[PDB]
Image (cartoon, rainbow over all chains, first blue to last red):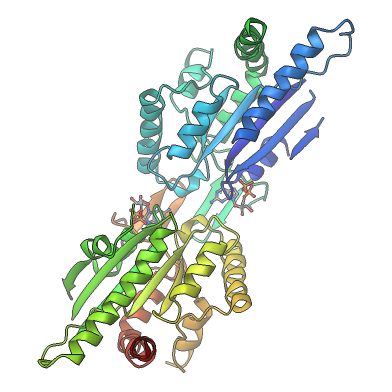
Amino acid sequence: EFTLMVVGESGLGKSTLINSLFLSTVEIEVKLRLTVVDTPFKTIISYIDEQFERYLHDESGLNRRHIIDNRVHCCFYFISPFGHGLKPLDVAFMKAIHNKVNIVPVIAKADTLTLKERERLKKRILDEIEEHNIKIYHLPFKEQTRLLKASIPFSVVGSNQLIEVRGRLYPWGVVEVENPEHNDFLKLRTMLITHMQDLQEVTQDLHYENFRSERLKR
Amino acid sequence: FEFTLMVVGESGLGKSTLINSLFLTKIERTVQIEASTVEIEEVKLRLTVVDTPCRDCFKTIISYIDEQFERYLHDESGLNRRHIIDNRVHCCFYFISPFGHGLKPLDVAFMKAIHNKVNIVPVIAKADTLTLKERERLKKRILDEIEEHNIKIYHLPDFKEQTRLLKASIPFSVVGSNQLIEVRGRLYPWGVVEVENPEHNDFLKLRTMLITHMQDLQEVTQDLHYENFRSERLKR
Ligand SMILES: Nc1nc2c(ncn2[C@@H]2O[C@H](COP(=O)(O)OP(=O)(O)O)[C@@H](O)[C@H]2O)c(=O)[nH]1
Ligand SMILES: Nc1nc2c(ncn2[C@@H]2O[C@H](COP(=O)(O)OP(=O)(O)O)[C@@H](O)[C@H]2O)c(=O)[nH]1
């Protein structure tokens, strides 16, 4: 029972990555719900909040032994590799929903950046995360958990096309989706796969209860 | 000899980097587009780069195009005409993002706004984000959209094969780099994009076409766009 939202500018490979992970709400079979949404927000917030209402209403009921959890457990936020950081629309969106959903920031179409360019954009996005007091999902073995945090935000490449593993062909070379020397796709997936319970659990224990307390107080 | 080259398009599309490669070096008022204009001698060249998005920015560019027409009309209407300084925009690279499936309707209306006043040369920026197959689909979608909407881009005139193959590339999909490599280029873990490598991208054609068509761009600007502006202007 798990729900993942992907949000971001149109044309940033949002759909291709989702397809790459698993090989406007689609529901494939754990039971995964995916909600892809292209940025141009008062409906996005409201969708998220509406899933807390159903759940609060449902858990408040006399019949429970068929409750559907539609709460969004994670939101990949896609950032253009063309900016030098977060655009203020991106910051405003993330601030609108950071108290309600687990944000995982992702740099899109990372095959657009040299390694030097990549690390400048990551450093700059992390600093802006701090500067604007934005609350992104924080990961909870030794060195593999070390290396994964030290590469947030993940800069990914999607493709489901094959190359004489999946990749993208340019006259000067081939980007390999699952080569970590090429991009953080494997890390993002592994992280998604290894952290589902926590994602679910932080959604329950933190975002939903905060929703719930303000409600029963008001 | 005087040439003014303008480049417009969203920021983050490599526009300065491209310009740098050709030679190796809130917008709301005509004034600040002038302040953006750099002058180099390489022939007196002026480069005028304008980040587009807020659609007032498009109105200022238009107003700016005309002001250069105005300067000229005013200067040739006066009594001392020895050096009329020609600041009329002879060319507009229009950078389109490789992330769209074509032109947005803003681009379309804007190009319709400026297409009887400057020579639009459309350019797909950051072409190293596109596989060759993607490159073709975007080129065709962009040309279709120009037909569909009757956008008048600059028609290259007409050793033999060099004109055909150059036309075939329009709109040119280009790559710029300030960095050098072993060539100006872009180093990725998987390979190196070479700017001047025509297999890799159409930069070589853009520069060659500019270098080669500069006189005709100037002339079309004079004989067509300018005289069109001047006829309309005097009527009022
Ligand atoms: N350079 C690059 N291009 C990509 C990548 N992923 C997808 N694309 C291209 O971008 C197009 C749009 O991707 P899409 O998933 O539809 O983006 P979306 O609008 O955010 O869902 C795809 O058809 C691919 O041709 C990537 O990782 N790198
Ligand atoms: N992938 C790619 N990146 C580029 C290209 N040209 C420039 N860049 C990168 O994009 C950054 C910003 O480009 P810039 O020229 O300042 O874009 P402008 O805002 O349109 O003037 C540069 O520092 C380069 O890192 C290109 O052809 N391809």
